[PDB]
């Protein structure tokens, strides 16, 4: 069923809450035993948001290999994503260790450091060229190279140095700065523009490790980003773009991380983004 017609049928009937609860009921439940070990309590931002054991990213160290991060592997679309929480004061070094070890080119940030008057993640990148950051626990150095501030997003060029080997890599930081403190954006136009800027950079391409995507918990806004990207890629590959079922793609992604899409309003916004996405790239 063409999703644009499914959309108007749900809107006219006002059944968004009913559709959303059906997804919550059918979603996978897999063990997260490593996340719940007592040694890992200060590595989790939220007690109710944990990576599954089968899909968690492992840090390359013998001490403690745990980080709140999941590998989302989309077999038909041929895309992979790492979805993670906003870094905590004691996990900023783990975060950059993961970017290094997984060979990621891009980090996608969908939150502000402060929202609703409370801290939603650590200040984990340098704000001035001449004041670099050193992470002594993981032996990494991070330097701000350049910053491009636009109305709806900022892009940063960062240099990550493995102090152990003196190898360096260029990381691109894509910061979506205008998601509202409450609800979802009225139009998906600026979110879509942002998504196609991340693509144009190479950060989502198979010649690099998976993109790292985060918000505060790494399930709601983060879920919206990967769901829109994968659905638009499937519409480009298939003989019948009308066969793409957004609810079935979301349930496949929920095999790899719990809770993706946190509200019925985020589910409706994801439909709106894909639908408009299709028109721009398939109509005109
Ligand atoms: C669906 C959509 C919306 C916006 C948008 C794109 C796609 C992106 C980039 C422009 O922003 C450039 N681009 C094209 O010219 C073809 C499509 N793709």
Image: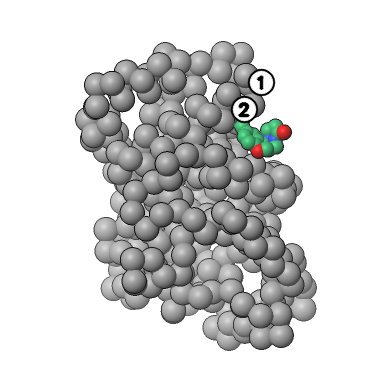
Asked if marks 1 and 2 touch (Cβ < 8 Å), the reply is yes
Query: 10 Å neighbourhood of mark 2: few (<14), some, or many (≥20)?
Result: few
- The quadrant of the rendering that contains the N terminus is top left
Decide: few, some or many residues near mark 1? Use Cα within 10 Å; few <14, some 14-19, many ≥20: few
Going by the image, does 40 lie left or right of 158? left
Q: Position of residue 203 (x, y in %)?
A: 67, 50
Q: Which residue is mark 1?
A: 284
Dot 2 beta carbon under 8 Å from ligand 1: yes
- Image quadrant in which you'd find residue 42: bottom left
Q: Residue 270, percent across and down?
A: 43, 36
- 236 relative to 220, above or below: above
- Mark 1 lies on a secondary structure that is loop
Q: Which residue is mark 2?
A: 280
Q: Residue at x 62, y 27 (%)?
A: 280
Q: Residue at x 23, y 34 (%)?
A: 17
Instruction: Residue 108 in the image: state x and y as whole percent.
Output: 56, 56
């Amino acid at each position: 069923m063409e999703m644009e017609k499914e959309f108007e049928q749900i809107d006219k009937s006002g059944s968004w809450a009913a559709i959303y609860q059906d997804i919550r009921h059918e979603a996978s439940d897999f063990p997260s035993r490593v996340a719940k070990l007592p040694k890992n309590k200060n590595r989790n931002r939220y007690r109710d948001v944990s990576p599954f054991d089968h899909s968690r990213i492992k840090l390359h160290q013998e001490d403690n290999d745990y980080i709140n991060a999941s590998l989302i592997k989309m077999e038909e679309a041929q895309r992979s994503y790492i979805l993670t929480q906003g870094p905590l004061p004691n996990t900023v070094g783990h975060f950059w260790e993961m970017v290094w070890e997984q060979k990621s080119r891009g980090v996608v940030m969908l939150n502000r450091v402060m929202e609703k008057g409370s801290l939603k993640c650590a200040q984990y990148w340098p704000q001035k060229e001449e004041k670099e950051m050193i992470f002594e626990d993981t032996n990494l150095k991070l330097t701000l190279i350049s910053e491009d501030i636009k109305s709806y997003y900022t892009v940063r060029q960062l240099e990550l140095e493995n102090l152990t080997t003196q190898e360096t890599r260029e990381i691109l930081h894509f910061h979506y700065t205008t998601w509202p403190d409450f609800g979802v954006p009225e139009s998906p136009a600026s979110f879509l523009n942002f998504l196609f800027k991340v693509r144009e950079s190479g950060s989502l391409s198979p010649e690099h490790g998976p993109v790292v995507v985060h918000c505060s918990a790494g399930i709601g806004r983060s879920g919206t980003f990967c769901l829109a990207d994968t659905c638009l890629l499937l519409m480009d590959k298939r003989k019948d773009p009308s066969s793409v079922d957004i609810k079935k793609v979301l349930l496949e992604m929920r095999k790899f991380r719990m809770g993706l899409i946190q509200t019925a309003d985020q589910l409706r916004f994801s439909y709106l983004a894909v639908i408009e996405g299709a028109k721009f790239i398939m109509g005109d």
